[PDB]
Structure formats: C-alpha cells, structure tokens
Image 1 (tube, rainbow, N blue to C red):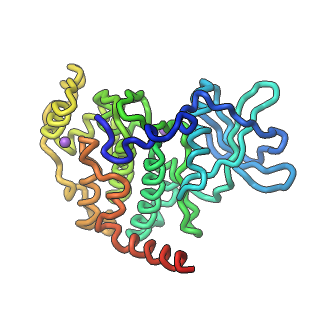
Image 2 (image 1 turned 90 degrees about the vertical axis):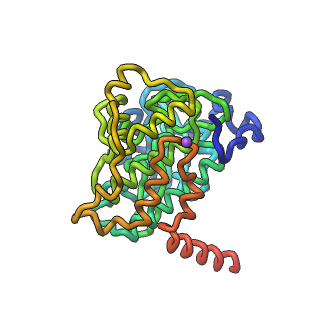
Image 3 (image 1 turned 180 degrees about the vertical axis):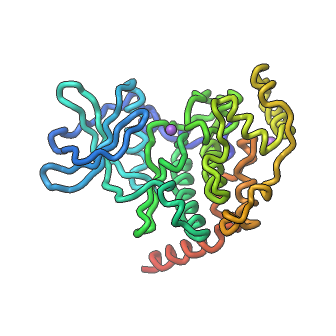
Length: 335
Ligand code: NA
Ligand code: NA
C-alpha cells in the first residue's frame, strides 16, 4: 500500500528534513524556565504551566519521561518542521537537566481546554467550525510528509474565546515514506484504525482520518468513545458490529491479510448497523444528513477509500465554514 496523496514529500525532500535519528539537538538553557503549576500527567510526559524566569512570560513545559533518544529527536524534528503551520502547536525551546539530562520541551502558552471539556457547551455550528480547523492542521502536516498517529480529543486544544484550535502532542508522529512498514502500536485504542488492528504495517496519513471519524461520531452521537473495545482484538469487534464483516472481508482480501484465528472467532459475522440507528432525542440537534454522509466517508475499513483531510474540507457539511474562511482569506490577500 502507498498513500494516494502527498506520497513523495519525503522522497523529494533531502535526508536533513526527515532523518531525525541524525539530528544534532540545539539545546537551550534549562535555567531560563521554572515550573509554575501542574497541568496533566500522561503516559510519556508530564505537562506543566511554566514561566521564563527572565521575562515572566508564560509557557507550557512538557517534561518527557525516560524514552529512547530517537523518539525525543523525532518529536523535536517534527515540531520544528511544522512550526508556524496552521493550528499546529508552536515549539519555543528545548532544554535538559544538567544532572539527569532529562529533556523538556517548551511551548507557547495555549490558554485552552481539550476538545472533550468543551463538548457539553458546543452547538452544531461550533462542531463544524472546530472540525474544519482540525482538518486544516491535518492537511498541513500530511502535506509536509507527517502523520500524527494520535488524533483524539485530548490532543486537540481549543481557546474557545479566540476560536483557536491547536493539534498537540506530536510524540507518536512519524514521517511518511512510501513503502515503509510502521509499528502498529500507535494511537489510543478507541481511535485506532483497522489497519492497526489487522497488522497492515504500510499505512499512511489516512490513519489520522479514521481517528478523526471516531472523534466525530462520538461528538455528534454523544457516545464517547464511539468504538469502546476492551483490548486491540475487541476494538476490531466493536468496529465490525457497526461497519459489518462483508467489507472487512473485502479489506483483508485486497491487502493480502489473514486474520489471526483467535481474532477471526472473536469478530464472527455481522451485518452493518446504519448510522441513523445512533440518532436519539438527545443528539438529534447535532445530526444531519450531511453529517452522516461525511462520517460514513471517514469510517471506511479501506484506508485508501477514506476522505483525505483536504477532501473532507470540501464536503457539503463544511460548505458554510469553508466559504467564511475563503472570504476572510480574500480580504487579507487584497490588504
Ligand atoms: Na495516546
Ligand atoms: Na476498498
């Protein structure tokens, strides 16, 4: 399998762009920063609000847990390559402790909450707006040869007053090289695409579009997580109970994959459950025929069949939000 969009970005670009294992990290000065307040704990890092001790400027300090140097260099290189792109978090500095050599990443202060915190106070219009903003981040990173590989509500930070979205936590992101077999142990279970669950290792940017579809289904149907499996096998079972097993058979045959016998027995046989069966009185204000059609075009087993980020932005569901962006950009271009 190879990506059908942005296929050769890292073939055309030289090794200095994507060869993160060779990066010579330009460390800043740890003494410039001080932790102020803990913000969150995660599997690979702890996040704090911090300050520059020289200027009192606020920042976010992400203290990385012990991991291989290659993974740290990867995140740094990706953040450096994407810095300044639309709706991508901005890396400001990289420092490490004098004695332990533990690295920290220093980011702009984001002044935001994650997408889930916002769910209860968002309307249909706000969902269309913020999903479009997330699509802009994904189209940009994909266009720069990078897959995020961990799209989920906690990695989408929103400053709701400024109507500003940022895609954060690039620690699982990778460069896309056509032909490369990647580790399938990425993303978070409920957002893993079927490629990760059937051991299709030569996946691409389209993984992020599955993850986005899972987020979108959870939002519009008020069912979080939408696919709630109890392990990686059961995650495929939950998907198959909705998409059905006929299309799973087609996918496996197309990519010359054989389900593990245990997984085959767990998945069994299932007819599809139409999207309309998830509508109820409590979520109907967020659902429309356009929303269902958009979702259906994201949640396809075959990664090549899914909408790309740019194709998603052109879907009728976003027609008004796209038009508003186009008009704004026009006036700024005339200015
Ligand atoms: Na994760
Ligand atoms: Na297909």
